[PDB]
Length: 258
Ligand SMILES: C[N+](C)(C)CCOP(=O)(O)O
Image 1 (cartoon, rainbow, N blue to C red):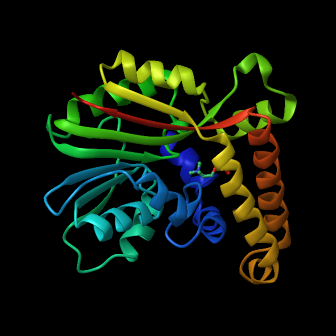
Image 2 (image 1 turned 90 degrees about the vertical axis):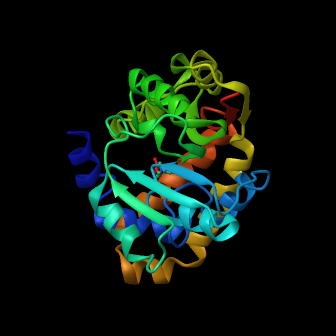
């Protein structure tokens, strides 16, 4: 299954901790806390709001949203191990819930959420399933609700080089263009669809992370291994190179139900 693939490879316990080291405490999403602050900078919610976080990971996003706004946050992630980790980092807070489930089968009421939020998680879904997911999101949003997404995107497949092809294949990602992604949202009837190619900003975030990794190599080696360091270092190097030339892209999407 997809769950087994993710838990046994990219998102083993150790894989998750390695990612957390570079992204920052409670994050496996690009730019950790700082990108979260920026992405939510024009979003308004309050203590009565209901938020869904698709691919909630280590829970930092939900923690931040609940801290900033006092909103109810419900995170869903397919990896049981990551959800277990997230649940270890929050206590005594009845407005944060993390649930291990498949978002493609999970049931939520129509007109339920003020915000549906997702950070670098939908890349794992096939194109067919991306469309199915956004149809569900449309239903699940309140009439007054907002959809807010970042995700890994790419140039057209015809332009990919050997190394990028191998990365996408090994990861089992389905990476589409920012423009194709926006078109899915439009096709799902979302209004006010705003898409931004934030590859340059993503490149900046990657550079901050890369510098951090290099400056904290000794600590990393104590926690992990040189082999894992090299893999991480090389992985960020490629993302930096590929975002600079727009082969690997970072898409931002915001839309509304009405
Ligand atoms: C996709 N992610 C941002 C959740 C984790 C990192 O994946 P990757 O950049 O190593 O492919």
